């Protein structure tokens, strides 16, 4: 009543290595181990080997010594239990004469997640720190947080923070960097101590620290200034006249996070704004993926102080190499940035755009022409003019979206465009989309007076009804009515059928209603209905768009942040 | 003048490999030198490389290279070369009739050899490649060999012939000859082969009657003998003799008694025994049963016996370990359409499976369970289906909806329930439900004129907390509209009304439009509805007019349009509102 | 900020990685790929994906998706810069990134990784500024007119480029994919003026059986970056063809349930699901349902489309004009008193394959423009389904 | 009937394939991988039977080694399983407490063994010994070929 084949510790893989591990020649042990981790990562099971591996500990040559480590390393978060069993080995390693080593012993100790860890490492930590080497300090600085984040802190722990700060500004090389952030992150779990970052002296520490190059540092530093500045001017002018190099300097992250503050702090202004210009720009001649985030922020930016690049735009055009998201945002922006002197070019470009091949694009693109005309009333026709201009191309897809837009246009500037109507219908077949068709229809309805044919057009769709997007079924109904109320005597049978279909031959509650509703309005008092339906129609309002006040100010803080992209509050992320 | 590597040696070398690139290297360098070794066609070492190759292949590499030469081994005199060879064939061959003939050749030449294991290779190989033409050739040769009683061979042969049949239906004739005696043999091996041989044979109605009437009784005895006694150091596998043999037997018994009284009527005994007399300990046995059951099913037999069969599967379901349970369900379905009244005796436990952690089971469970929904059943099972549905995983939700609906749509008690349930489902899947729902459910409500209350009621409650959902909300908003009347703490039958402040009715509707979670269509039903209330209430007839006129300016061509429409209705021809709304028509199925 | 970094291979399976913090890692990464794809169906393809409040920062480099993870509100800008840098480093250590590459230097990577950052915050890193912190060296891996006469005319310069894909499939009641084939074709139509060099950029994604171009094509400068430059004849011609082998969840599934007896009547119920990205829809689709040679008289009832019958060929035909993706419609028909069921469709602006034309350039001496139209269609008919 | 069988470890490493039904090489490798992926991919908690491409598949996990095969729907999954366990059985007693490595280094034999256990998609013997006993003497013949 016992069975387990292919599971002998007499031979095979496991064994093979196991032995070849304990041999002599330092070489074997080395390679051997290597295969281990390897053979590990791919997904095999090394639960076994563990022992004999560690016990390949009491050796020396870095080579081996570290490999061993890595191994253990992986086992970090996975099976912490095993990690621990190595403790002693580490502590006792902390003292080793090769900081490199003892440092690793640190970082290592630190990548565990169990409570039992507190006991064994703390003391050695303090030590390792105050000690004498770059890596050493850095590394533990890091740890600190790790310990913090551990499922618990201590009354000693809340005493290491001091170590931090003090040791922070002090020890000089990159170290500080780590320290900084270390704390920063720690801070956010905000009791009090995170709020005493209020020194217009501790700041100069940071000041010279920025010019003491560790990009990552540069950031973390700025990243902190995002918790400051209550009330004074001379300090502002120096804090900022100090960041001026930061922009033209290194890698985005910098420039960005840098800006992140420049704007939380705001003959003063003109200096900033005319400098802030060439930075953001050269920020885009950079790379694909980044470009996004920035644009996203760029957006948020002009939203607050548009005055910054009020005329810089011969750049925000979309090239072909540029990926989709790129393009998208680029648009959204261009838009939030046009006026008279602008539009001239704006359109010129949109037109070409539309000509492109990437569908989606052209779409939002034409749709751009749309929002465009809206913001700049003073440029209505102008747009239209080109819209129409495109449809004359009979490029199936373009066409439809186009119309759609035009529709919306009419909603805002009624009885101002007509002639365009006939020229419109022209392409009636080629329109196979919902809203597209829909829209089209509803249009006819409204401006029925003009088109004689009105009838058949609408009619056309009928025979092929009982099936077409809900929404379209609607207007179509509505519309019909409309012209019927333009009194045509010839409308009888039509309207009749219409309702009729949308009366009993249809199975969409809502529909049935708006349907019946009319059937009663008419079966009772035409004159009445007339005024009713085609009644003086109100003005439209989609001011619901283009960011808010309270919210705007608040966001700018998180540039280079996730929020920096969603344009939303940490409340939606945090879970 | 080379120094040829040896197989293992090779591999062991690829074990040293540190980089995929390198692997190529080594390999490429190997086969390269190996090719230049075949240039000469040197009889010795021939075997080796072929192997080397084999391996090479196995690791997904340039194989074709030596298909041919592989055969040139088969040629060789020395056994070895032949086995290594043959093996290589089965692996590296494309079905070229050309080699196929060369194959044929060597097969025969080998099939008639002084030694015997040679003959082994042959047979074997032939039963694994045998392409039409082949068989059409060696066919007879197979019989000549089928005869000679050297157990080892015979069994091999048997199977061969089989394979032949499979590729050349036309020839089973010449095998009638081996037939008659076969089922009397003593060595399991053969016997077994012999069986499937027979089994496969019976794919031509006539032969049936031959074996049908013949061997049936005998088969029995054999099987019986087995089951019934002794432990066997040669055959047992955890307490039973040659399960295999046992199974296959069953199978054959099964197939024979397909549709017939005589046969069956003559089997039901051994069967029953097989059932009662076997060990439920571990799988092995159960395997036995699994088969026995299937057999017991396709064949006519006392109502009492079939009953046992079923009750047996149930017995499975309740087994600690997955596996088993699977088939348990599977087969179960294939018979629900037949032994309905019989299986029912277990649903309770079946649906109880839905609680399992394995998709397959789940589904099947479901599928079936469903099917068992009776009349007097529904209520219960539904209550369970519902619990289920609610916590289910996406995949399923979708399909179940469809399911429940059915149930209710067909076998179904009260509307209140029907609705209650349908709604219920919406409440949980909606986002997954098909399209016709919205109208569906309403049509149900409208048609049955009582629960009008009970409905708007619950409808209301649900919507108060929830928002997430569309179909649901819609439906509600609907009635709320058309039914506001009744929604006002009315003299409600079927059950207990609640607090209906018109202000509240609105608050909800209002939020609906505002909150971003609703579709333009949604907002529709709403607004429209809100107005339907103007005629259906007594006092807040003002907050109403306010809203309407505000929406008169919304992006939604529709909403607006209507808004204006309504708006204007108040502003001018009031009293029409009363007659206009107060009447919702009614469509009937 | 960043709490995890992975490195995957196209497939989206975890290739090799390191965990610098505390998030159920084990899962999420797995969901990656799946999500990715869907969010590409919505076109709303963002380098920042979402799953339950878990964000993904990624970058695709030849053959390898590189990714980051965070529960908190990250400093994106970073992560992105960093990641990209990560490449920088590797590519330097051994010639080029590629599954293969990684598959080799695992170890060192584990090292490198560790020294590149810690607990998230990246303790700085640049090549030389590092080679001291790294144990051993890694292994590198370096690898590798006449058809248009001349002086052509016509006032309006225009172009037509149409890619089409038909989908041959077979599935038995056992709801399994049996054959997965989609033949593609980039037919093109043109009437440009003169001699214009045409540059065509492509989607990435395009296991693959055969691929044949038209001589007039050239593969844009050696490696991995897809660009298809060439000079087209006049009129119509096939720019390129190809066949793929891939489990394509049956675009338009179906399944018929049966129910017969009492007064020699029989009932059919057919569900027809549309397995697609919701955003688009299939056209002029039609369903051919096999039925008994000897029906008496039918009675169809359906929410959608119109169904009809034809004793000849013995089949009930469900016809639908427009059909959206992601929705299931129901058809049920009875009558009174086995060949596989097929259907033919058409789906504008769609590519089962997954390609998308990226961009079409036109460069001519005549500093002019031109008008290019595209169309994507996934039709076909070998769409056959069984019933035993 | 058996449609075919394979031997691969956790990671998609083919250790032994054997096809019982004519087929083009390409299609094979296809079959292979296509399966392996969807095969392995499953949690150890789940079951041992899957319905794939019309056929019924089966497998049992032996340490870092997978055993798979396909059957015709009209067949007994369970019993099949017991077959595998039988093969392994053989393998074991032949190499003495067998293990993966072995299989990689001696597939050849692995085949023979198997090959002379199952033929044309079925069971040729059951006798744990019948097979061994035979397979053994065969080997003796082999030896006698190099060493006269």
Image (cartoon, rainbow, N blue to C red):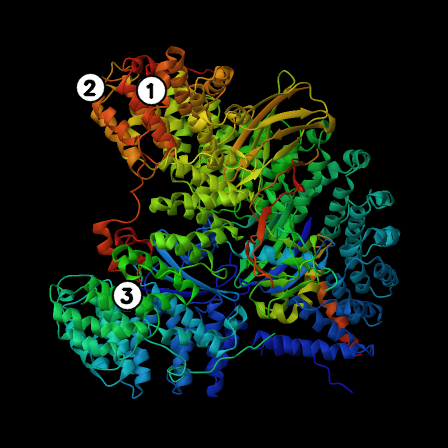
Residue nearer the viewer, C142 or C207: C142
Give the image location of residue A574, x and y in percent: 28, 54
Q: Is residue C169 left or right of residue A26?
A: right
Q: Is residue C263 left or right of residue D23?
A: left
Labels 3 and 1 in the same subunit: no
- What residue appears at the point 47 percent right and 69 percent down from the top-left corner? A40
Q: Is residue A163 left or right of residue B560?
A: left
* Pair 1/2: label in front: 2
Residue sitting farthest toward the left: A231
Residue nearer the viewer, C79 or A234: A234
Residue wearing tag 1: B482
- Crowding around mark 3 (Cα neighbors within 10 Å: few <14, some 14 to 19, many 20+) is some
Q: Could you tell me which secondary element the residue under label 3 belongs to?
A: loop
Residue wearing tag 3: A114
Give the image location of residue C100, x and y in percent: 54, 71
Please tell me the numbered disc located at residue B539.
2
Mark 3 and mark 1: Cα distance apart in space: 62 Å
Residue sitting farthest toward the top: A524
Quadrant of residue A244 in the image?
bottom left
Q: Chain of mark 3?
A: A
- Crowding around mark 2 (Cα neighbors within 10 Å: few <14, some 14 to 19, many 20+) is few
Mark 1 and mark 2: Cα distance apart in space: 17 Å
């Amino acid at each position: 009543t016992d069975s387990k084949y292919f599971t002998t510790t007499k031979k095979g893989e496991i064994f093979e290595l196991k032995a070849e591990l304990n041999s002599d020649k330092k070489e074997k042990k080395k390679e051997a181990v290597k295969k281990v981790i390897a053979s590990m990562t791919v997904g095999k099971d090394v639960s076994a080997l563990f022992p004999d591996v560690v016990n390949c500990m009491q050796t020396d040559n870095l080579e081996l010594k570290k490999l061993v480590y890595l191994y253990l390393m992986n086992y970090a978060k996975s099976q912490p239990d095993m990690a621990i069993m190595a403790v002693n080995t580490f502590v006792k390693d902390c003292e080793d004469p090769n900081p490199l080593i003892r440092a690793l012993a640190v970082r290592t100790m630190g990548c565990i997640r169990v409570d039992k860890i507190t006991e064994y490492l703390c003391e050695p930590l303090r030590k390792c720190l105050k000690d004498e080497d770059p890596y050493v300090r850095k590394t533990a600085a890091v740890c600190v947080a790790k310990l913090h984040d551990i499922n618990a802190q201590m009354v000693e722990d809340q005493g290491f923070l001091d170590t931090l700060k003090d040791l922070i500004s002090d020890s000089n090389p990159m170290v500080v960097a780590n320290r900084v952030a270390a704390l920063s992150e720690i801070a956010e779990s905000h009791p009090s101590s995170n709020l005493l970052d209020l020194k217009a002296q501790s700041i100069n520490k940071l000041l010279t620290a920025l010019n003491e190059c560790t990009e990552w540092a540069q950031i973390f530093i700025l990243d902190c200034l995002g918790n400051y500045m209550p009330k004074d001017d001379r300090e502002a002018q120096s804090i900022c006249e100090r960041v001026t190099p930061r922009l033209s300097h290194a890698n985005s992250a910098v420039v960005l996070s840098a800006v992140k503050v420049l704007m939380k702090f705001m003959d003063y202004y003109a200096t900033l704004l005319k400098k802030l210009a060439p930075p953001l720009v050269t920020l885009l001649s950079a790379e694909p993926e980044p470009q996004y985030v920035p644009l996203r922020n760029i957006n948020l930016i002009v939203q607050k102080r548009p005055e910054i690049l009020k005329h810089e735009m011969k750049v925000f055009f979309v090239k072909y190499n540029d990926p989709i998201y790129v393009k998208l945002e680029k648009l959204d922006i261009m838009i939030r940035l046009a006026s008279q002197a602008n539009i001239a070019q704006v359109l010129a470009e949109l037109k070409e755009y539309a000509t492109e091949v990437d569908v989606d694009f052209v779409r939002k693109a034409v749709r751009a022409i749309g929002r465009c005309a809206i913001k700049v009333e003073q440029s209505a026709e102008r747009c239209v003019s080109t819209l129409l201009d495109l449809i004359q191309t009979k490029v199936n897809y373009v066409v439809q979206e186009a119309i759609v837009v035009i529709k919306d246009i009419f909603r805002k500037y009624p009885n101002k465009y007509e002639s365009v109507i006939a020229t419109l219908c022209e392409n009636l077949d080629s329109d196979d989309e919902p809203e597209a068709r829909a829209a089209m229809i509803w249009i006819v309805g409204e401006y029925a007076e003009r088109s004689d044919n009105a009838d058949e057009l609408l009619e056309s769709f009928l025979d092929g009804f009982h099936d077409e997007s809900t929404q379209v079924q609607l207007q179509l109904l509505t519309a019909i009515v409309k012209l019927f109320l333009k009194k045509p005597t010839e409308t009888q049978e039509l309207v009749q059928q219409v309702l009729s279909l949308a009366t009993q031959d249809s199975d969409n509650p809502d529909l049935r209603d708006r349907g019946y509703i009319y059937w009663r309005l008419l079966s009772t008092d035409p004159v009445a209905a007339k005024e009713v339906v085609l009644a003086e129609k109100p003005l439209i309002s989609e001011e619901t768009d283009l960011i808010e006040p309270t919210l705007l100010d608040e966001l700018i803080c998180y540039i280079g942040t996730l929020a920096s992209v969603y344009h939303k509050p940490p409340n939606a992320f945090v879970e | 003048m080379p120094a040829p590597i040896r197989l293992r040696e090779l591999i062991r070398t690829i074990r040293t490999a540190r980089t995929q690139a390198e692997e190529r290297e080594m390999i490429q360098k190997e086969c390269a030198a190996i090719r230049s070794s075949f240039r000469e066609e040197d009889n010795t070492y021939r075997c080796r490389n072929v192997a080397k190759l084999l391996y090479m292949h196995m690791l997904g590499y340039p194989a074709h290279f030596g298909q041919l030469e592989c055969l040139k081994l088969i040629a060789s005199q020395k056994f070895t070369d032949k086995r290594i060879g043959y093996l290589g064939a089965m692996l590296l061959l494309d079905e070229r009739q050309d080699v196929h003939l060369l194959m044929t050749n060597c097969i025969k030449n080998d099939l008639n050899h002084s030694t015997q294991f040679v003959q082994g290779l042959a047979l074997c190989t032939l039963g694994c490649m045998g392409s039409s033409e082949m068989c059409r050739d060696l066919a007879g040769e197979v019989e000549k060999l089928l005869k000679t009683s050297n157990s080892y061979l015979r069994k091999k042969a048997a199977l061969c012939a089989v394979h032949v049949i499979r590729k050349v239906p036309e020839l089973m004739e010449m095998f009638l000859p081996a037939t008659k005696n076969l089922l009397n043999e003593k060595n399991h091996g053969v016997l077994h082969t012999s069986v499937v041989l027979l089994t496969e044979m019976c794919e031509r109605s006539p032969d049936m009657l031959a074996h049908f009437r013949k061997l049936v009784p005998q088969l029995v005895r054999i099987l019986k003998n087995l089951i019934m006694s002794g432990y066997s150091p040669e055959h047992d596998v955890s307490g039973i003799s040659d399960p295999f043999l046992q199974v296959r037997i069953l199978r054959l018994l099964r197939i024979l008694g397909r549709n017939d009284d005589d046969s069956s009527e003559a089997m039901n005994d051994i069967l029953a025994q097989v059932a009662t007399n076997t060990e439920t300990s571990k799988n092995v046995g159960n395997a036995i049963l699994y088969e026995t059951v299937l057999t017991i099913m396709d064949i006519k037999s006392e109502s009492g016996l079939r009953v046992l069969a079923i009750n047996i599967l149930g017995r499975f379901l309740l087994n600690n370990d997955k596996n088993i349970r699977y088939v348990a369900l599977t087969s179960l379905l294939k018979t629900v359409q037949t032994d309905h009244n019989a299986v029912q005796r277990h649903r309770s436990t079946i649906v109880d499976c839905l609680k399992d952690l394995d998709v397959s089971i789940k589904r099947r469970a479901m599928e079936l369970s469903f099917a068992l929904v009776n009349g007097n059943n529904i209520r219960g099972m539904m209550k369970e289906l519902l619990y289920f549905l609610d916590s289910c995983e996406p995949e399923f939700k979708a399909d179940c909806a469809s399911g429940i609906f059915l149930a209710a749509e067909k076998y179904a008690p009260s509307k209140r329930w029907h609705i209650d349930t349908i709604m219920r489902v919406l409440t949980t899947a909606g986002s997954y439900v098909r399209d016709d729902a919205v109208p569906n459910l309403i049509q149900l409500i409208t048609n049955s004129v009582e629960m009008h209350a009970y409905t708007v009621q619950r409808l209301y409650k649900a919507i108060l907390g929830d928002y997430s959902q569309q179909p649901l909300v819609q439906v509600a908003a609907w009635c709320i509209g058309e039914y506001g009347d009744l929604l006002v703490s009315g003299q409600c039958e079927e059950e207990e009304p609640i607090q209906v402040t018109e202000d509240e009715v609105l608050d909800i509707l209002e939020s609906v439009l505002i909150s971003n979670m609703s579709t333009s269509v949604t907002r529709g039903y709403a607004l429209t509805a809100i107005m339907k209330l103007s005629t259906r209430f007594t006092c807040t007839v003002n907050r109403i007019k306010k809203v309407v006129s505000i929406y008169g300016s919304s992006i939604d061509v529709e909403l607006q349009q209507r808004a204006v429409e309504y708006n204007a209705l108040f502003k001018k021809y009031d009293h029409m509102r009363s007659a206009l709304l107060e009447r919702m028509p009614v469509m009937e199925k | 900020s960043a709490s995890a970094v992975y490195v995957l291979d196209l497939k989206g399976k975890v290739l090799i990685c390191r965990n610098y913090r505390g998030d159920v890692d084990m899962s999420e990464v797995e969901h990656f790929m799946p999500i990715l794809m869907e969010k590409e169906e919505e076109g709303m393809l963002s380098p920042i994906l979402a799953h339950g409040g878990v964000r993904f920062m990624w970058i695709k480099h030849n053959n390898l998706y590189l990714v980051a993870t965070s529960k908190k509100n990250a400093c994106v800008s970073l992560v992105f810069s960093f990641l990209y840098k990560v490449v920088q480093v590797f590519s330097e250590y051994f010639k080029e990134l590629e599954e293969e590459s990684i598959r080799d230097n695992f170890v060192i990577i584990y090292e490198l990784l560790d020294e590149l950052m810690d607990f998230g915050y990246p303790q700085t890193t640049d090549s030389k500024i590092l080679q001291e912190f790294i144990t051993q060296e890694g292994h590198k891996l370096e690898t590798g007119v006449s058809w248009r006469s001349e002086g052509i005319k016509y006032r309006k310069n225009e172009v037509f480029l149409d890619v089409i894909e038909a989908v041959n499939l077979l599935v038995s009641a056992n709801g399994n994919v049996l054959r997965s084939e989609i033949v593609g074709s980039i037919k093109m139509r043109v009437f440009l003026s003169g001699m214009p060099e045409l540059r065509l950029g492509l989607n990435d994604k395009v296991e693959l059986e055969d691929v044949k171009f038209h001589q007039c094509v050239r593969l844009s400068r050696f490696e991995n970056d897809r660009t298809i430059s060439f000079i087209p004849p006049d009129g119509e011609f096939e720019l390129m063809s190809y066949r793929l082998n891939t489990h394509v969840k049956p675009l338009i599934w179906i399944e018929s349930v049966i129910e017969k007896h009492s007064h020699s009547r029989i009932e059919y119920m057919v569900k027809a699901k549309s397995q697609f990205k919701r955003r688009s829809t299939a056209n002029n689709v039609e369903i051919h349902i096999p039925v008994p040679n000897d029906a008496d008289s039918p009675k169809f009832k359906t929410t959608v489309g119109s169904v009809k019958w034809v004793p000849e060929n013995s089949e009930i035909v469900w016809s639908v004009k427009s059909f959206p993706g992601g929705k299931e419609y129901l058809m049920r028909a009875h009558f009174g008193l086995k060949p596989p069921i097929s259907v033919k469709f058409e789906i504008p602006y769609f590519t089962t394959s997954g390609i998308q034309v990226r961009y079409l350039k036109i460069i001519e001496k005549s500093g002019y423009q031109a008008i290019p139209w595209v169309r994507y269609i996934t039709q076909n008919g070998d769409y056959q389904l069984r019933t035993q | 009937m058996m449609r075919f069988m394979l031997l691969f470890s956790r990671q998609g490493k083919l250790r032994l394939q054997k096809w019982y039904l004519a087929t083009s090489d390409k299609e094979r490798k296809k079959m292979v991988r296509e399966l392996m992926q969807v095969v392995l991919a499953r949690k150890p908690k789940m079951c041992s039977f899957l319905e794939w491409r019309d056929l019924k598949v089966v497998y049992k996990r032996y340490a870092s080694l997978y055993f798979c095969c396909a059957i015709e729907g009209q067949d007994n999954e369970l019993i099949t399983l017991e077959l595998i366990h039988r093969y392994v059985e053989l393998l074991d007693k032949y190499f003495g407490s067998v293990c993966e490595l072995d299989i990689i280094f001696n597939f050849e034999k692995a085949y023979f063994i198997l090959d002379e256990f199952l033929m044309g998609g079925d069971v040729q013997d059951t006798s744990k010994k019948s097979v061994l006993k035979a397979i053994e003497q065969a080997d003796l013949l082999q030896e006698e070929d190099e060493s006269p």
